[PDB]
Image (cartoon, rainbow, N blue to C red):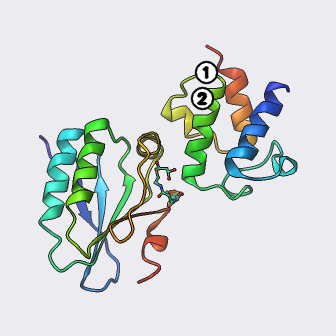
Amino acid sequence: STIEERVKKIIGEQLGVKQEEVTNNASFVEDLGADSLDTVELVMALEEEFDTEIPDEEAEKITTVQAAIDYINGHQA
Amino acid sequence: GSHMTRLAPVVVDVPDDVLVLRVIGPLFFAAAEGLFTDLESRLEGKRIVILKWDAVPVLDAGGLDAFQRFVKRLPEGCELRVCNVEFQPLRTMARAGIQPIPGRLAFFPNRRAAMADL
């Protein structure tokens, strides 16, 4: 899979929604039925898969599919 | 201690056996110790205690320890309800595997949900 596909796959798994619904625009809470704990677990799963610690201030902004994709691609240091 | 982590009154109509407070400030060990010790003195005749944590930006390992001990020590028939847990404390508690405890500890997204059976 591509990185974008991998991010979407993980979002789908963590939030328990079909891959079809994990569109780039989608907000975890407003669109994909997530709550704040689902969101925390989702960030944790991204941290583990991509071998990176995400600071709280930045993690707090990962609230949509695109946001997650953008952070992963953009923060590889 | 500058008493910067504190319990604040909440203006809401509730039964006399329900206590609703905000926690304002970080729950680092030392501050948490003082806050939960204070809270324990306010529990007489209370069936439900609701803590809104919107203004708790951080919870550290010792602060969590203090929270767990506070919960362990709650009187029989008194349930702690915590709402509006922010990202860092929520991630901290998730990593620690904190779970609700029937009749003793429950979590809610917001005050409305925490007060829905009232």
Q: Chain of mark 2?
A: A
* Nearer to me, A27 or B39: B39
Snapshot quadrant of residue A67? top right
The quarter in which the N terminus of chain B is drawn is: top left
Q: The residue tagged with tag 2: helix, strand or loop?
A: helix
Give the alpha-carbon distance from disc 2 to disc 1, as whole Å: 6 Å
On screen, A3 above or below A20?
Answer: above
Residue lying at the far right in this picture: please name it. Answer: A20
Residue at image point 45% right, 82% down? B117
Residue in the foreground of this view, choosing between B71 and B53: B71
- In the image, residue B89 above or below residue A4: below
Q: Position of residue A58 (x, y in %)?
A: 56, 32
| Residue located 25% across and 82% down the image | B17
Q: Is residue A59 above or below residue B99?
A: above
The image shows residue A33, relative to residue B96, as above or below, that is below
- Foreground: A68 or A12? A12
Q: What residue sits right under mark 1 in the picture? A: A51
Q: How many marks?
A: 2
Which three-letter amino acid code belongs to the residue tagged 1?
Answer: Asp
The amino acid beneath tag 2 is Glu
How dense is the environment of label 2, judged by Cα within 10 Å: few (below 14), some, or many (20 and up)?
A: some
Estimate the x, y position of residue A14 in percent, counting from the top left: 67, 46
Q: Residues within 10 Å of mark 1 (few under 14, many from 20)?
A: few
